[PDB]
Image (cartoon, rainbow, N blue to C red; front, side, top):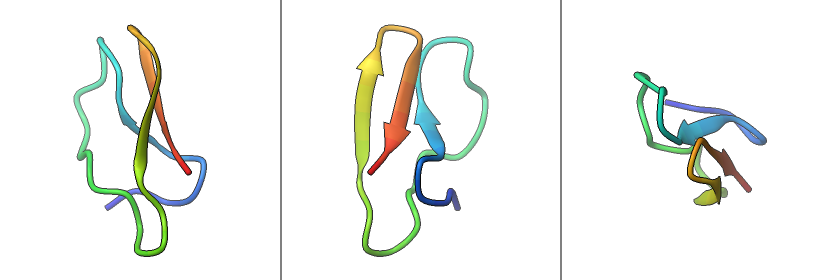
Length: 36
């Protein structure tokens, strides 16, 4: 799982995309998605 302000997605990312409870995944740009 990811933590708050954690990268859940974004090109080049090869990690889990599930944000910690209480948060959600938010695409920042086509190369980064933060969890807020």
